[PDB]
Image (spheres, coloured by chain):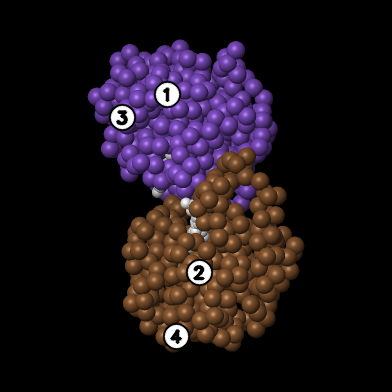
Chain colours: A purple, B brown
Amino acid sequence: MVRISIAGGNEIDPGSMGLTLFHEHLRLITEVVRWNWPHLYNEDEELKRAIDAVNAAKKYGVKTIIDLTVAGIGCDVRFNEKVAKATGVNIIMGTGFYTYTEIPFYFKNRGIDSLVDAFVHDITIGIQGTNTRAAFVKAVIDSSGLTKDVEMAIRAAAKAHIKTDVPIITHSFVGNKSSLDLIRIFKEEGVDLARTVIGHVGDTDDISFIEQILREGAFIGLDRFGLDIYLPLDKRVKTAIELIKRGWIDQLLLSHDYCPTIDWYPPEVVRSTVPDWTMTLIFEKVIPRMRSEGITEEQINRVLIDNPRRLFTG
Amino acid sequence: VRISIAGGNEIDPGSMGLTLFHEHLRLITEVVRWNWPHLYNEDEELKRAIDAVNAAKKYGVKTIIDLTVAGIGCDVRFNEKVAKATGVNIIMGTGFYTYTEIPFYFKNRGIDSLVDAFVHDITIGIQGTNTRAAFVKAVIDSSGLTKDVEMAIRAAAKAHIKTDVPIITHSFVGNKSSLDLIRIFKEEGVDLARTVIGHVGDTDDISFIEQILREGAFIGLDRFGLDIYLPLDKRVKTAIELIKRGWIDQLLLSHDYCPTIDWYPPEVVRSTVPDWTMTLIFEKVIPRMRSEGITEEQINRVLIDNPRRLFTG
Ligand SMILES: CCCCCCCC(=O)CC(=O)N[C@H]1CCOC1=O
Ligand SMILES: CCCCCCCC(=O)CC(=O)N[C@H]1CCOC1=O
Ligand SMILES: [Co+2]
Ligand SMILES: [Co+2]
Ligand SMILES: [Co+2]
Ligand SMILES: [Co+2]
């Protein structure tokens, strides 16, 4: 009975998601740069890179990818439709506003409701003039902390969840404990935390801090496998195995946050700095290592199939 | 000098004629337009832009310099439609409009990547077209000189040094940020005669204004009709006084008019600055200045020769 729009305006139910990567990207670009300086980009090559990435995940049994690209990081339904068509993978899209500091004057001068309404439109009508609806909302906080504008956008994500019941999938930054501001704001807004992911929690191996989040009842995103600059692979794998052994499995989500294009850094820089980052590292290295430490096949399926499904059905 | 105008034709500075040096055709926020097109109507935007430029045209305006750059919604194709419907020359530029931050794309690559982007626009073309940028914009406002704002100002200066296009600025007089533009341009070796210090008309403080003028730059008395920044009568008195005090060759007049501005609902704009248009200088400013002894030829020096000299030096 829950219906999830997917890139192309089809719908699936949560039961047919199957093996899912809950936080990945197809193309991460900056709208104001791309609009004004198209010569710095190449759409054919972006498309090839996203297709190649998704096909690689698909060879390992991925059926569904949740694209966490929203406004501010270059969301494009038409791009995603080409990717979906070429690959046959389900692509789930969302809404929200991605920022660490400021929001546009457009919404600041109109008030929080204007931002909620834009999100609700994407969820109930469709994204960017299409019939693909947003099936989740994103809230973002980072190293600048809880600025007024960031607070507004997090609260607008919350209010949009209260009106539509779509899950809230977040970005946080663990070094300043911003993860906890998400939870506090969500509690104030009456959000059921079981319908939320506190993101980028896998960027720390501090288990007591992770449990402080877990005891509030939310999902956590162990979601940057392959980005050693946030936390090395060995510590991420160790953390995930330990959290399963301690009884936290129903709250764990795994992903790579992989960006087949990311315009924030030259591609040479990304290759030099995180050469292991792909959309398949979980299947190549993480799962084999977890299996060798006693994690079961069914535990892996609970994480990669049942948890993403339950985020969408409750 | 050859000046590209929207459409990729080129004009020489002599053919600019009566020029509005700081206006807009459409001021919108790229990230919002890209993500929520349902909040916009392109036919209506076009119509408002055309109507505004045709009103100006009625008063003899031949050329409008569109100060819309990256950050506030610049679109060559939109402008080409306006140019073609109206017959008015539209001159475009490049730069990055921000009061605080610049994109990660540029911050992680460094200053040269932003310079090169501007230079691309000036020497090859804007947005895949053959309309080249004819000026570069630099911006500072009430947040002051942040690190990113400083970078973008210095990048505009460096692009000016490579290409010799003029620099038309935005500043905020309330914190004296106008003076940071000046200091930075001097450090970069810019001839200030090739620059406009923008939004100076937002104050009637003669001493502050003369501090800028003695540096040799043009000043933008460029928001006629925005009473919320400064009432029309103070703007008019200030312009008359500056002419009388000998500064005519450094004065530029405009309205900063936005036929669309997505920062505010249209009803709030109508309600707050109902006299804001792209023709108020012709309807009210010029008749008041003439009644105070300002001559016809003085008016032409400000509205014809000054914009020309900005492009020729
Ligand atoms: C030198 C920097 C090396 C490149 C590392 C890549 C950094 C990232 O791309 C992290 C990242 O993805 N942050 C953004 C993009 C996905 O959504 C986010 O929150
Ligand atoms: C509260 C309602 C304010 C109504 C008028 C707002 C007018 C402006 O926003 C002036 C303005 O355009 N400033 C921006 C945009 C043109 O270049 C600028 O720097
Ligand atoms: Co993130
Ligand atoms: Co991400
Ligand atoms: Co301005
Ligand atoms: Co302006």
Query: Please, which chain is the residue tagged with disc 1 on?
Result: A
* Labels 1 and 3: the sequence-earlier one: 3
Farthest residue in the left direction? A208
How dense is the environment of label 2, judged by Cα within 10 Å: few (below 14), some, or many (20 and up)?
A: many
* Labels 2 and 4: the sequence-earlier one: 2
Seen in the image, is A141 located left or right of residue B95? Answer: left
Seen in the image, is A1 located left or right of residue A270? Answer: right
Q: Nearer the viewer, residue A23 or B261?
A: B261
Q: Amino acid at mark 1?
A: Thr
Disc 2 + disc 3, Cβ < 8 Å? no
In percent of width and height, residue B107 lies at 41, 56
Numbered label tally: 4
Seen in the image, is B81 located left or right of residue A234? Answer: right
Q: Amino acid at mark 4?
A: Lys
Q: Amino acid at mark 2?
A: Asp
Nearer the camera: disc 3 or disc 4:
4
Q: Which quarter of the picture shows residue A17?
A: top right
According to the picture, the residue beneath numbered tag 3 turns out to be: A180
The CA distance from mark 2 to mark 3 is: 47 Å
